[PDB]
Image (tube, rainbow, N blue to C red; front, side, top):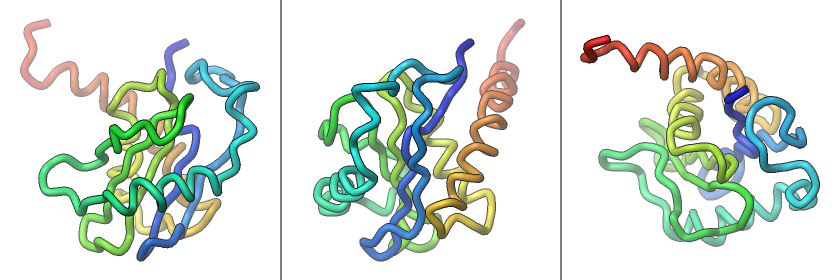
Length: 149
């Protein structure tokens, strides 16, 4: 099937990871990418990627929300960064799969903002998945706002 899955969701508070959603899967039924040549990297690689690339080039969003570094931090996954809706010292960096378009990670971070919890290396991951399922529902709902049929 054609589903989604944020490979690694590393949150950041004051330039320091607060939460993290780093869990392997080996492309189960979401998106073909990780399975062997993308399950060795440690959250630190991404945590340092972000911190060393994203953080030193992050922004509190002015009218984008969940923007990809477009710097090619690493190969195999897609890396974007979304700062808190009211706390620049509370970023939200996601590490989806290159196969994954540029819309899930957007709903993931913006989604975590839908809740009130996302400050643990096993909490944000929650809404990430709970937002993942509801994500598509939005993609479907999105196909009926101003269309003919």
